[PDB]
Image (tube, rainbow over all chains, first blue to last red; front, top):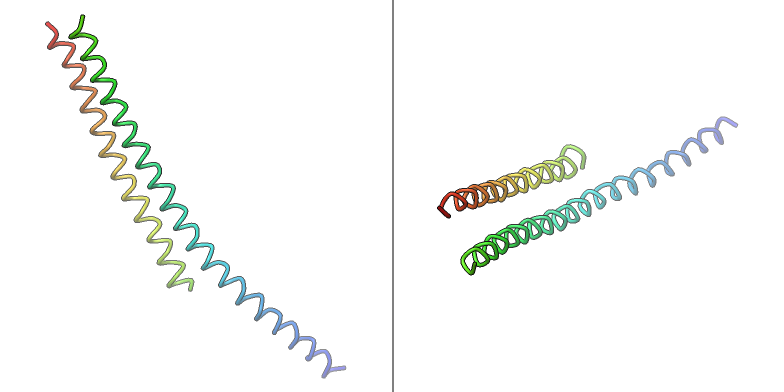
Length: 70
Length: 46
């Protein structure tokens, strides 16, 4: 019974090994995927800000044209 | 992993966020400068 109790301990340790390795690899992959997704999101935000700048420039040009034509 | 890859990825995320914040601040500075130019363009109508 001592042998089998420590054998159950050994089995739990091996299961914990597999779980720990899988969790560490999953954490690393999740961090990498989060970094890539954040890169994509910030690139999209930068593009949207540039588009907003272009929109403001267009507003200025339209206002100038409207005033000059009047 | 923790002190290395995970910490390095977190630091890279923070650096990317800082660079994005700097770019956003520059874009907003351009926005405010253009708005001030337009406000002055009101005065230049006279």
